[PDB]
Every structure is written in C-alpha cells, then in structure tokens.
Amino acid sequence: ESQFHDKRIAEELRTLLNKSNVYALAAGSLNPYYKRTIMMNEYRAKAALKKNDFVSMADAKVALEKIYKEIDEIINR
C-alpha cells in the first residue's frame, strides 16, 4: 500500500530557531552535549528550510522542542 503526505508548510521552526540562540546561551552552564546538540540541529533545520523538504523540517522540529524541554527542566529544577 503506497501513501504520500505532501508539502503544505505551516510550521514556524522560525519560531523555534528564533530562540535557538538564547537556549544555546543557557546551555553554557551545562555539559557541552546540550550546546553541541543545538549547534547541530540548527544546521539541519536551516538546510531543510532552504530545500523546503517536509520530512527534514518535521524532524528538526521534534528535535528542537525536545532539547528545549530538557534544558527548561534542568534549569528550573
């Protein structure tokens, strides 16, 4: 059974990558893992916006909400 989802794009990973730098700043009291993982998700997200690929955009989005949630948690205690 073949199936296709298509490119109707209504995601603001803009919104996420808008704070991608503030979150980078706040991981600077944490293991290098956290910053490094922002540095390497920013990349994916940007390329993905440029080629307008859906699946790369959805990935990166999930990735960023996850790491922001981790950071928040850690920081709030």
Image (cartoon, grey):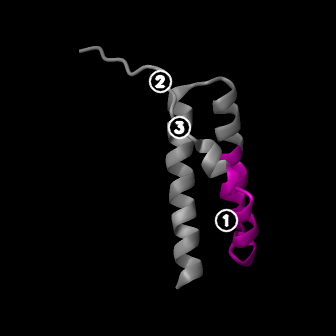
Q: In the structure shown, which secondary structural element does the residue marked by tag 1 occupy?
A: helix
Q: Describe residue 3's horizontal placement relative to residue 44 as left or right.
A: left
Mark 1–mark 3 CB contact (< 8 Å): no
- The x, y position of residue 14, in whole percent, is 64, 43
Q: What's the magenta bit mostly, secondary-structure-wise?
A: helix
Query: Which picture quadrant has residue 1?
Result: top left
Per the rendered image, the range of residues in magenta is 18-42
Q: Residue furthest top?
A: 2
Q: Residue 40 at what x, y percent from top left?
A: 69, 49
Gap in angstroms between the C-alphas marked 1 and 3 = 26 Å
Would you name the residue on which mark 1 appears?
Answer: 33
Q: How far across and how far down the image is residue 20, in percent?
A: 69, 55
Circle 2 sits on which residue?
8
**Was residue 58 drawn as part of the magenta stretch in this picture?**
no
Q: Mark 3 highlights which residue?
A: 11
Counting residues from the start of the chain, the first of labels 2 and 1 encountered is: 2
